[PDB]
Image (spheres, rainbow, N blue to C red):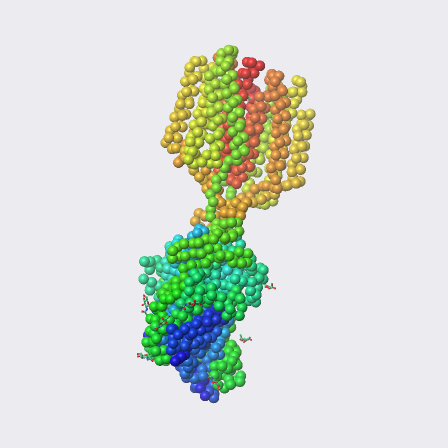
């Protein structure tokens, strides 16, 4: 001969978990009687001696010791359903060279082979669902997820394995959260960081509290997705008895549980010659009324694994096993490592002692959990079955609420009203030019220089034109045509001002020199130095377009899009120097024109002095241009007010300097 | 005579805690002193059968099998390491054996329903928690993080610590745990920005934890660690092949971390039941050791192993038959249990008694790693709540690192250089106003000064002086005054500037108005009109200030990083006066004054050509009101747009007052003083 195996199972009915042990005996006997009919082991025969371990760490270790002392020479250990005694037995296998093979231990701590080098496991562990969750995330483009872990050994180990599974992939963990008794002193942080996909690792009675608090933060609905473990008892939500059950069902509807698949759905023949459905029928007619345990297929495959491992180990060959033979234990271990065959639960194959099996997904509908897909770990594939998976929204919940850049626009009605007003300014300027050019022969106009007037009307006509180029933002102007228009507008404005005032200062020069074609040459010499200034400007810093983005916070109108306001403007390395040079040159010209006008007004020229008009217009321009320069450069981060000021001051100044020069003569001609 | 009563023992010589390197010579001595005395047990002889558990329960299971299934029957078991002690104490009830652990600190072993036949001379690890909560309360820390290895001892210690901090108002904001690789929880601690960390794990695991901490940069000025003081005094300098960090690199990662332990040795020079003081015991144990105590593991817990043997002997003494004991009979077990339970005696570790909670040592020692060597920073007794601080804890910067970088609320003030400059300008402006007033009232009627209406110009200069001295309240920020004196600066702005503008514009508006409406004359109506204007203005201002008083209001801005230091992230908040409803009263006031200014400009333009001699200089008055109107209509909405920028608003108000008040006084008075007395 006999080859003895030590089965350690809770067989008594006093324990609640014994319903597992009494569920798998109908299955194991189906494997034992088969092996003896086809006689895989020809000279020997397999016998599994059962020992009751009621999951007490006291009674199970007692049974293990009494089986070691008073029992036959056991070659392997089989079973172990409760993890408290299973870890105790599995950690000590090295002292007797026994190789244990469990079928119901799923805690991930048994996965490391520095602490449990002789332990094998036929059921997929708890941390075997992470590769399935990864393929589920890659199937819906969920590249950013948060986690909610309960601080105990099993769940913390699942989380620590998940951290290493996603490493190397594009998926990102936003925030890791943990709790021990109160789960929603931490759900508020998942709501504050605004994670849309939450991976939960917590027990059964904490899930009800997690969901009843997620109902409070409204962490449910068409924009949130929960992926929790699915090994919970069926109808686990009915057993929670202050929180309403209707709100719990409304908050939990749609979660995707992940758990191992009991039996394979493939119809190919297994190692025993029967298909999984034939084995399932044989099992359901083998046990009369005993409760069906979900571990029966794994016990069947475990017995077949033991049979094949003993076959390969005895063909590898000391015949007896006095628990001291290290070579025989090592041979059995190496023969167990090479297990590879198709059984009723899929392809049984081990990778570092852990089973590579299939993991199913179950989504929660109205009052049930329906299967929605399966992940095969040997082929590393995810097959989501059609028509069964659904979401409360039209599309699957997206993570990373969209951020988008939008320009802070100059209001179109304000630009419209001021562009409609400046064209009225230009048409009245053109009407005054018509008045000047039609009545050029009367002595009331010939007393003044009629050409130094049609230069100032040109200056005002094109400095009115400059208002539009201050409103072109980028809602309707591209990169390069904005960048070059930004210096076209400064040429326009500066040459308009310089002509418009140099012409009246030349007109005053003439009347001051006579009383004690040459009038155009000095305004040309002023434009010479103006264009020299602005070419020295353009050669150093051409006013490259910059764009400032700030305040990524503001909420939308309600369509769930985080709008990021940003705005574009013209700057350079240091605009202060260039603006100061331009304004200082223009102010020097202004003061040296007012001086020469005051010398003319000191002697009272009878009918063409006009120096009071020069004084008033120069005063208004000197105050309003300084104000418009100092207010436009301090309201740059709010461009609508900036434009409404820099356009209004231009309108006011270029209308005053035209009217106070032109209307006093038309009012005495007519 | 001399019937050998054997005891089983498991001494860990290596592993997570090598206590057996000195706890074995402790019992090997304690068995000789108890067997040499005739009054303790004359008929029996205590003998020891020991193995090496190495803190590994896998070896402990095999050795417990070899102990419980060999011919010589053992009367009691003595496990060491916590996992071995839990295994033995939970399994022993199937053989009716007493368990007496000398070095187990797991708080989970205190319940008598799960371990009904267990005793320990070692105190429970829940004595570290009151000291930790006291050190958290002393330094004002409210948010701590934890990282522990998932052993039952550390899990139960962390649960008790959680209960204690929840009682005291402290919150555990982050929680990490690992089985054999701490890289992931350390990286999560660094990502979560944990400041005050509490580590609950063995030394062999502590070396790996701190190597990943060094590679992760989770040390320095911002972080402080609370470890357990049971490690060797050089655990970070020991060569270890499983961990990469060089010892010189790891000495920086462990720096300034606080560690708590228990005294476990009676400092009094009194003699115990064994007739030896603590110092003689330490000296004899050091003579029995192969190497210095500074390199022998478990040297701190040896008094407990010494006292456990004496407790066992004194409990077997009060029960006096012991050879009939077998694993199938519980009467001898119950007798020995009731004899152990009622044990109370003065041993080397003080008053030894087996209470249910396991708390008999009161003093806890606190120390800190300073420069690669531990220094004792104080002691604490939680039963009396008294903390003896030695004042020797060194910190980087002289203060304990505070967690949770808070918000510091700072105010934005006016640059005092600018305020002082404008105040000097206003002082010179009021002295100019008083000079021109003394001039124009000295020559009251000495010359043609009476041809111009003199009192209107005089009280115009008065209103100008008030409106120009009204810049000091408008510049007084919270830097000079404080909150309690503040609400009067607001009314000292409003009344001064309102009355000043009314008195300095209505007085030279009524002159223009009378020039217009009688020259296109009466001596007292020129005062009646300005009195009506100023009185109605004061009525319209008092109704606003009394119906809706102006009070301080803070406008808070978004957070910014004041990283000119290495300190807290502040948020700036500006303070300025406002009414309960604003921009409606001030808007209507501005609109009315702008309408008056427009009407004044119109009347000054319509009467610029009249050549009356009942009034001397209405043209300079017209120029003055034009300039005042343009300046005020420009700088009224500008300070409404730039309200959230203190310096720009103050400059555009104060300079728009100073220039206007200089121009009006010049334009009115320098022509008259120039032509009158040249
Ligand atoms: C307010 C006051 C000083 C009376 C004045 C105002 C104007 C405005 C056209 C701007 C309204 C004005 C004059 C004086 C002039 O006599 C001049 F001197 F400026 F030429 C003129 O016609 O324009
Ligand atoms: C193991 O077998 C050897 C060989 O017969 C024997 O000498 C020894 O006593 C046995 N030991 C045990 C524990 O069975
Ligand atoms: C099984 O384990 C051995 C080492 O004992 C290794 O050399 C071999 O590659 C493994 N084969 C597998 C994993 O199938
Ligand atoms: C689902 O399976 C059917 C086969 O019956 C196939 O036609 C269909 O394309 C599948 N759906 C998707 C989304 O691939
Ligand atoms: C037991 O030991 C004590 C001393 O510890 C001794 O006084 C006593 O006499 C002994 N037992 C009896 C009953 O004599
Ligand atoms: C670990 O440390 C060793 C010795 O300093 C070094 O050679 C090695 O590169 C380190 N680890 C890695 C990433 O290789
Ligand atoms: C205890 O030992 C000391 C050391 O010599 C001795 O002086 C004293 O008399 C002893 N007392 C008892 C009661 O044994
Ligand atoms: C053994 O235990 C039984 C329990 O009833 C007791 O009656 C008997 O005296 C004991 N005999 C011994 C201690 O050998
Ligand atoms: C041991 O003494 C304590 C002290 O009150 C008591 O509560 C307990 O019941 C005693 N143990 C037994 C087994 O009676
Ligand atoms: N008093 C020694 C005790 C031994 C143990 O509990 O295994 C111990 C507990 C915790 C640490 Cl970190 C180190 C040692």
Q: Which image quarter holds the C terminus of chain A?
A: top right
Please report the residue visible at 35 percent of the width from the left and 58 percent of the height from the top: A247
Please report the residue visible at 66 percent of the width from the left and 30 percent of the height from the top: A526
In what quadrant does ligand 7 lie? bottom left
Q: Position of residue B11 (x, y in %)?
A: 47, 72
Q: Can residue B523 be seen from the camera position used here?
A: yes
Q: Is residue B564 above or below residue B499?
A: below
Give the tally of numbered discs: 0
Q: Is residue B175 above or below residue A662?
A: below
Q: Is residue B558 left or right of residue A205?
A: right
Residue toward you, A55 or A423 = A55
Q: Position of residue A141 (x, y in %)?
A: 49, 60
Please report the residue visible at 45 percent of the width from the left and 15 percent of the height from the top: B518
Would you identify the image quadrant in which residue A522 lies? Answer: top right
Residue toward you, A94 or B605 = A94
Q: Position of residue B407 (x, y in %)?
A: 47, 46
Please report the residue visible at 68 percent of the width from the left and 32 percent of the height from the top: A528
Q: Position of residue A57 (x, y in %)?
A: 39, 73
Q: Can residue A307 be seen from the camera position used here?
A: no
Residue toward you, B264 or A323 = B264
Residue toward you, A36 or A367 = A36
């Amino acid at each position: 001969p006999p080859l003895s195996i030590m089965g350690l199972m809770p067989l008594t009915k006093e324990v609640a978990k014994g319903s597992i042990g009494r569920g798998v005996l109908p299955a194991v006997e189906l494997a034992i009687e088969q092996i003896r009919n086809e006689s895989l082991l020809r000279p020997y025969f397999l016998d599994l001696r059962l020992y009751d371990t009621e999951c007490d760490n006291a009674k199970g270790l007692k049974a293990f010791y009494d089986a070691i002392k008073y029992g036959p020479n056991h070659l392997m250990v089989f079973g172990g359903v409760c993890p408290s005694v299973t870890s105790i037995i599995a950690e000590s296998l090295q002292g007797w060279n026994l190789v244990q093979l469990s079928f119901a231990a799923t805690t991930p701590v048994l996965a490391d082979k520095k602490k449990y080098p002789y332990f094998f496991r036929t059921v997929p562990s708890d941390n075997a669902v992470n590769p399935a969750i990864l393929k589920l995330l890659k199937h819906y483009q969920w590249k950013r997820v948060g986690t909610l872990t309960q601080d105990v050994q099993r769940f913390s180990e699942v989380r620590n394995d998940l951290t290493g599974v996603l490493y190397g992939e594009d998926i990102e963990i936003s925030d890791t959260e943990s709790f021990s008794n109160d789960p929603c002193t931490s759900v508020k942080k998942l709501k504050g960081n605004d994670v849309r996909i939450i991976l939960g690792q917590f027990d059964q009675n904490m899930a009800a509290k997690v969901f009843c608090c997620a109902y409070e933060e409204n962490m449910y609905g068409s924009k949130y997705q929960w992926i929790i473990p699915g090994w919970y008892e069926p109808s686990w939500w009915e057993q929670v008895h202050r929180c309403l059950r209707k709100n719990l069902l409304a908050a939990m509807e749609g979660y995707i549980g992940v758990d191992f698949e009991p039996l394979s759905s493939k119809q190919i023949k297994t190692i025993s010659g029967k298909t999984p459905q034939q084995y399932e029928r044989e099992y359901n007619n083998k046990r009369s009324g005993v409760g069906p345990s979900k571990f029966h297929g794994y016990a069947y495959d475990g017995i077949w694994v033991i049979a094949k491992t003993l076959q390969r180990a005895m063909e590898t060959l000391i015949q007896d096993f006095n628990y001291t033979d290290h070579t025989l234990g090592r041979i059995i271990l190496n023969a167990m490592n090479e297990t590879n065959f198709f059984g009723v639960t899929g392809q049984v194959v081990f990778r570092n002692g852990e089973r590579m099996g299939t993991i199913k997904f179950t989504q929660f509908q109205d009052s049930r959990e329906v299967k929605v897909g399966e992940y095969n770990a040997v082929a590393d594939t995810l097959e989501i079955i059609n028509d069964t998976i659904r979401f409360q929204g039209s599309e699957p919940p997206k993570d990373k609420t969209i951020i988008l850049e939008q320009l802070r626009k100059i209001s179109l009605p304000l630009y419209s009203i001021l562009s409609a007003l400046t064209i009225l300014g230009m048409i009245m300027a053109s009407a005054f030019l018509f008045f000047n050019i039609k009545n050029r022969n009367q002595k009331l106009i010939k007393m003044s220089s009629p050409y130094m007037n049609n230069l100032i009307i040109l200056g005002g006509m094109l400095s009115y034109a400059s208002i539009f180029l201050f409103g072109l933002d980028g809602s309707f102007v591209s990169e390069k045509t904005f960048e070059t228009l930004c210096t076209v507008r400064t040429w326009i404005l500066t040459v308009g001002y310089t002509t418009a005032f140099g012409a009246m200062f030349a007109k005053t020069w003439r009347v001051h020199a006579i009383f004690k074609q040459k009038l155009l040459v000095i305004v040309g010499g002023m434009l010479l130095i103006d264009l020299c200034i602005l070419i020295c400007w353009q050669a150093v810093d051409p006013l490259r377009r910059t764009v400032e983005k700030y305040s990524m916070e503001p909420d939308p109108a309600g369509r769930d899009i985080s709008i990021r306001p940003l705005l574009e403007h013209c700057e350079n390395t240091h605009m202060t120097i260039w603006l100061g040079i331009v304004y200082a040159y223009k102010g020097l010209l202004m003061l040296f024109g007012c001086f020469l006008a005051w010398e003319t007004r000191n002697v009272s020229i009878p009918a063409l002095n006009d120096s009071k008009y020069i004084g008033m217009s120069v005063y208004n321009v000197g105050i309003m241009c300084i104000i418009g320069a100092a207010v436009s450069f301090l309201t740059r981060d709010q461009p609508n007010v900036q434009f409404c000021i820099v356009a209004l001051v231009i309108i006011f100044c270029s209308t005053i300097t035209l009217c106070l020069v032109f209307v006093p003569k038309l009012i005495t001609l007519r | 005579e001399r019937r050998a009563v054997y005891i089983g023992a498991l001494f860990p010589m290596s592993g997570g805690w090598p206590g057996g390197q000195a706890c074995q010579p402790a019992v090997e001595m304690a068995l000789e002193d108890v067997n040499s005395r005739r009054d303790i047990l004359p008929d029996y002889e205590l003998k020891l059968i020991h193995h090496d558990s190495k803190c590994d329960p896998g070896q402990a299971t095999k050795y417990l099998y070899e102990l419980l299934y060999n011919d010589p029957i053992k009367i009691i078991l003595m496990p060491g390491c916590s996992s071995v002690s839990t295994l033995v104490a939970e399994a022993a009830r199937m053989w009716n054996l007493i368990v007496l652990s000398y070095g187990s600190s797991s708080p989970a072993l205190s319940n008598r329903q799960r371990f009904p036949t267990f005793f320990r001379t070692h105190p429970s690890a829940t004595l570290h928690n009151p000291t930790r909560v006291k050190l958290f309360e002393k330094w004002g820390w409210k948010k701590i993080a934890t990282i522990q290895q998932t052993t039952e001892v550390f899990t139960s210690t962390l649960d008790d610590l959680e209960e204690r901090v929840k009682e005291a108002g402290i919150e555990i904001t982050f929680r990490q745990s690992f089985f054999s690789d701490p890289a992931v929880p350390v990286k999560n601690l660094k990502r979560q920005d944990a400041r005050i960390i509490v580590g609950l794990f063995y030394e062999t695991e502590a070396r790996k934890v701190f190597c990943e901490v060094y590679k992760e940069r989770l040390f320095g000025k911002k972080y402080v660690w609370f470890l357990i003081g049971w490690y060797a005094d050089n655990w970070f300098k020991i060569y270890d092949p499983s961990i990469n960090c060089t010892v010189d690199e790891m000495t920086e990662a462990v720096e300034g971390h606080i560690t708590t332990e228990i005294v476990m040795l009676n400092p009094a020079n009194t003699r115990s039941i064994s007739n030896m003081t603590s110092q003689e015991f330490v000296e004899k144990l050091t003579k029995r050791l192969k190497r210095h105590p500074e390199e022998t593991g478990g040297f701190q817990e040896a008094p407990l192993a010494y006292d456990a043997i004496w407790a066992l002997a004194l409990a077997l003494n009060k029960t006096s038959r012991l050879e009939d004991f077998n694993y199938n009979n519980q009467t001898i077990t119950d007798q020995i249990y009731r004899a152990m339970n009622s044990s109370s005696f003065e041993g080397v570790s003080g008053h030894v008694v087996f209470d249910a909670s396991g708390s008999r040592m009161a003093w806890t020692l606190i120390e800190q790693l300073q420069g690669g060597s531990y220094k004792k920073i104080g002691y604490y007794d939680s039963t009396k709540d008294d903390l003896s601080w030695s004042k020797t804890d060194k910190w980087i910067g002289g203060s304990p690192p505070a967690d949770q970088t808070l918000v510091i609320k700072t105010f934005r003030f006016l640059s005092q250089k600018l305020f002082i400059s404008v105040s000097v300008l206003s002082s010179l402006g009021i002295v100019l106003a008083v000079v021109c007033l003394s001039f124009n009232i000295y020559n009251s009627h000495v010359r043609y000064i009476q041809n111009s209406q003199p009192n209107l110009n005089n009280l115009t200069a008065v209103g100008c002086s008030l409106a120009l001295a009204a810049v000091f309240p408008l510049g007084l920020d919270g830097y000079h005054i404080g909150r309690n004196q503040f609400p009067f600066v607001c009314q000292a702005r409003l009344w001064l500037l309102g009355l000043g503008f009314s008195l300095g514009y209505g007085s030279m508006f009524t002159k223009i108005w009378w020039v217009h409406t009688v020259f296109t004359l009466e001596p007292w109506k020129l005062y009646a009109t300005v009195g009506l204007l100023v009185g109605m203005d004061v009525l319209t201002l008092a109704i606003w200030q009394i119906v809706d008083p102006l009070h301080r209001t803070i406008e808070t801005f978004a957070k910014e990083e004041p990283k000119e230091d290495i300190d807290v992230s502040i948020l700036p908040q500006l303070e300025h006066c406002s009414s309960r409803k604003m921009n409606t009263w001030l808007g209507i006031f501005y609109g009315y004054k702008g309408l008056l200014l427009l009407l004044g400009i119109f009347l000054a333009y319509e009467t610029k050509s009249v050549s009356t001699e009942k009034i001397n200089d209405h043209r300079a008055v017209g120029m003055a009101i034009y300039n005042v109107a343009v300046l005020c209509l420009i700088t009224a909405p500008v300070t409404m747009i730039l309200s959230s920028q203190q310096d720009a608003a103050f400059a555009f108000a104060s300079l728009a007052i100073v220039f206007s008040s200089y121009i009006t006084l010049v334009v009115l008075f320098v022509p008259k003083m120039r032509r009158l007395i040249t």
